[PDB]
Image 1: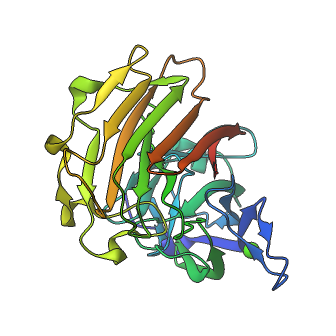
Image 2 (image 1 turned 180 degrees about the horizontal axis):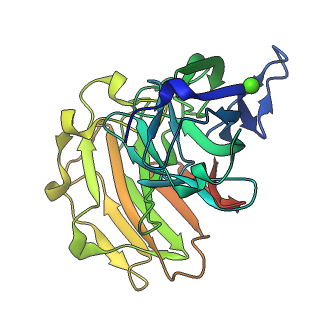
Length: 313
Ligand SMILES: [Ca+2]
């Protein structure tokens, strides 16, 4: 095959926020990634007649934008013609944030071939880290580049002693990969009982993927809830995580034997759906402290095959 990025022409390119939340102060539409929104990429295209089966073309996504929803994008990506046949089979590489498509025999079925597509998309959370910030969302389809500014707000309320979000949903097993932030305000406690209770999911203790990281720098609390754990101090083995209710409940005393603590923590967990008929469910967190019990909750909805997530106190 040949690279035919110069022979596949995209037009009417747009990035939508679905549904989008209007900021009642500025009047602008925002992307509230932890209040059920996703992005959508849409375009029409034409294909020169010299293109043949096996020729390739790319969608290159920019540093703040990726395909997928709360659920990470599939490695395999089909593009369908208006008749419902697969015109191109794609391979998405997360390291290069690029899908390479290979045309099928269907590109040779007709002359003057024309198609369109709508693809769910999202912020690249490890890069678009910060709330209430406009990010250039960019894509190059073939050789056609498009971008628009999208204000992202993940709702990381820094004054809250307990807040949690879905980091991502795994595309292969539909597991919820969670991030909870404990003590962003850096208060001092003598009691700190951290409880997670799952509805529709279970933990797997033997997988050793309930992780506790001690924060040493306030910037580690990225608003996107996708922190770079490779840079953090992994203190998990210092704590006793107690499972109950057939692995639906996890309890940990974050004081770990100390009389007083103003330590701050990032906690990551993996919650597996009970079965393959649905991945809906709910995750409830509580932090019981000296004089206050804090609560945060996470819920999900599937919309036309994209995963959406909502967190709330
Ligand atoms: Ca738009």
